[PDB]
Image (tube, rainbow, N blue to C red):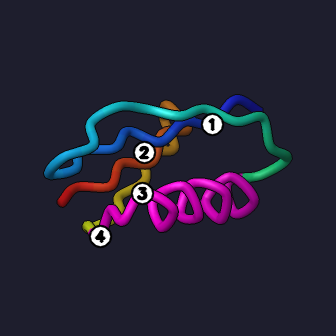
Amino acid sequence: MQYKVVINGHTLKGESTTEAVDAETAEKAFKQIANDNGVDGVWTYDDATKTFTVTE
């Protein structure tokens, strides 16, 4: 399944996508991306669009 993270950061604004078997797998990948970029925000998940949002 095609999952996406929308990054609403103070400095970094954008999106990343990954193919994953489930949302738990995708989530762990997107949290590492946020960690790698120092993005520290609140996480929400929208399963209608398989999209995570992290909002700083």
Check disc 3 and report its element: helix, strand or loop: loop
| Location of residue 20 with respect to 19 vertically, above or below | below
Q: Which mark is residue 37?
A: 3
Q: Is residue 50 left or right of residue 5?
A: right
Majority SS type along the magenta span: helix
Closer to the camera, 54 or 45? Answer: 54
User: Given the image, on which type of amino acid does mark 4 rest?
Assistant: Asp
Residue tagged by mark 4?
40
User: Which residues are drawn in magenta?
Assistant: 23-40
Check disc 1 and report its element: helix, strand or loop: strand
Seen at 54% across and 36% down, the residue is 4
Residue tagged by mark 1?
3
Instruction: Name the N-terminal-most of marks 2 and 1.
Output: 1
| Location of residue 16 with respect to 53 vertically, above or below | above
Q: Closer to us: mark 4 or mark 1? A: 4
| Location of residue 12 with respect to 25 vertically, above or below | above
Q: Which mark is residue 44?
A: none
